[PDB]
Image (cartoon, rainbow, N blue to C red):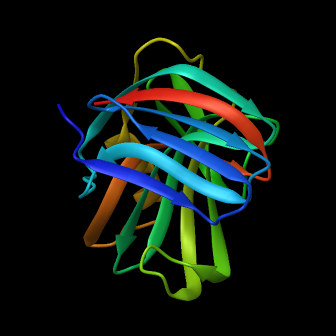
Amino acid sequence: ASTDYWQNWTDGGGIVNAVNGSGGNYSVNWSNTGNFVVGKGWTTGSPFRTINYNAGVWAPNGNGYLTLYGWTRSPLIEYYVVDSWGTYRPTGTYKGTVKSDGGTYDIYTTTRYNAPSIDGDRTTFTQYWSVRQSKRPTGSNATITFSNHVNAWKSHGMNLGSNWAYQVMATEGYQSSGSSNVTVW
């Protein structure tokens, strides 16, 4: 089922070379970056979507995340289902775990302050995380049964907004270099 959204954002730091590839495919070559988020997915997220991806290349050189990534408004939430990462495993306030798609994920919340949102405002907002406890193998088809995360998050008072923004399978990087090549459907 096809993606209709191209997420390609950089804070401008270093070099973030994103290729909007065929269909749900994209790749990113980055170097000496600030923060950036690139991915393919859907203009409107769903708590029911089953995201399929195949990360043919997951090669962060330093800090990057291979993560479902999206936003809601009402409330404003930036959320993650992190399947793999580079040198740094992201965490926050531990809530519990959720088992989904043969992985165990820790559930975290963080808050961002003085931080740009989807909507451009430098503001405050909460992040919801599922972060796999160990890195998911990459290079084969993988599913993120997002509903599992949604249900688990709900159980920990992490309610998503009623207004769904985009929902992408993303490469996010912080202060790093690397390569990714990911296909999403």
Comparing 72 with 57, the one in front is 57
Q: From this viewpoint, which residue is outermost toward the left? A: 1
- Horizontal side of 112 relative to 160 (left or right) equals right
Residue at 44% of width from left, 73% of height from top? 118
The reply to whether residue 59 is in sight is: yes
* Residue 84 image offset from top left, x and y in percent: 63, 32
Comparing 156 with 83, the one in front is 83
Count of all numbered marks drawn on residues in the image: 0
Q: In this view, does 170 lie above or below 58?
A: below
Q: Quadrant of residue 169?
A: top left
Q: Is residue 37 above or below residue 183?
A: below
Residue at 17% of width from left, 31% of height from top? 1
* Residue 141 image offset from top left, x and y in percent: 40, 15
> Quadrant location of the C terminus?
top left
* Residue 14 image offset from top left, x and y in percent: 74, 55
- Horizontal side of 25 relative to 60 (left or right) equals left
- Horizontal side of 61 relative to 7 (left or right) equals right
Comparing 51 with 15, the one in front is 15
Q: From this viewpoint, which residue is outermost toward the top? A: 140
The reply to whether residue 151 is in sight is: no
* Residue 39 image offset from top left, x and y in percent: 44, 44
Residue at 72% of width from left, 33% of height from top? 60
Residue at 42% of width from left, 80% of height from top? 119
